[PDB]
Length: 30
Length: 29
Length: 29
Image 1 (cartoon, helix red, strand yellow):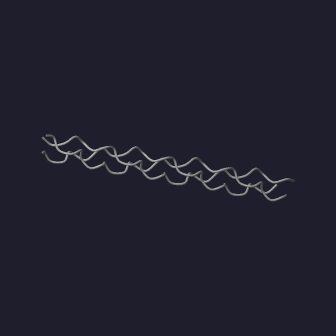
Image 2 (cartoon, one colour):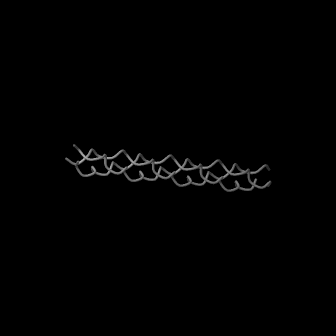
């Protein structure tokens, strides 16, 4: 008979960079 | 015969943090 | 019985990373 299924594969590639962050706080008062 | 190929591996690591956000709005006068 | 089969494929790409840091303060008013 055919042998056992092979080992599971390796982990996949790292995911994409996340979305850009939120805007910063409003600037200092004039 | 040799067995079947194994199952796909686990999902990869989460991605890195995203880029910093934009500068905030200009301040009040 | 036969030898174990080939290793499986690499897994799927991971999830997107976290949102990036908040941006810096805005320009002075």
